[PDB]
Amino acid sequence: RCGAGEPWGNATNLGVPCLHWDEVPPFLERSPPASWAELRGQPHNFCRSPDGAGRPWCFYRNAQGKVDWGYCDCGQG
C-alpha cells in the first residue's frame, strides 16, 4: 500500500529509519540534492519534500554509523 509521493514517515522509502533533521552531522556522507535548511523539520524526523516534483525524502541513519538520504516513496528507489 505504497503510492509514489507518499512517505512511509520515518523510513527512507521502505528501508532505513529517518534521523532527525537537526541531528544531521555537518560532515555528511551523502550530498543532498537541495538546500534542506528550509525543510524546517529540525526538531523532529520525518520525510520532507524540497523537490517541486512532490518527491519526499529524508536522511536515514544505519547501524554502520552512516547518515545518508533516500526518497520516501516506499517503492521508487
Image: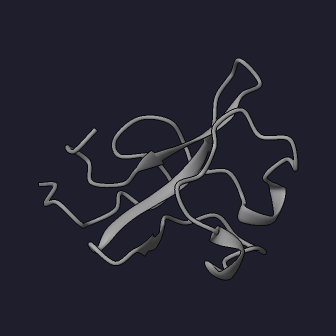
37 up-or-down from 12: above or below: below
Q: Is residue 37 left or right of residue 76?
A: right
Picture quarter containing residue 76?
top left
The residue sitting at 17% across, 60% down in the picture is 4
Q: Position of residue 31 (x, y in %)?
A: 63, 43
- At a point 29% along the width and 74% down the height, the residue shown is 54
Q: How many marks?
A: 0
Which residue is drawn at the image coordinates 27% and 72% (left, top)? 53
Q: Quadrant of the C terminus?
A: top left
Left or right of 13, for residue 24: right
Determine the residue located farthest toward the top in the rendered image. Answer: 64
- Relative to residue 45, is residue 70 depicted above or below? above
Q: Nearer the viewer, residue 75 or 36?
A: 36
Q: Pinpoint residue 12: horizontal percent, then vertical percent.
A: 44, 46
Figure quadrant of the N terminus? bottom left
Q: Toward the viewer: 50 or 41?
A: 50
Q: How is the image coloured?
A: one colour
Q: Residue furthest right?
A: 26
Relative vertical location of residue 74 with respect to residue 23 in this rendering, above or below: above
Residue 44: x %, y % from top left = 70, 70
Residue at 26% over, 48% down? 74
Q: Quadrant of residue 9?
A: bottom left
Seen from the viewer's position, the closer of residues 73 and 32 is: 32
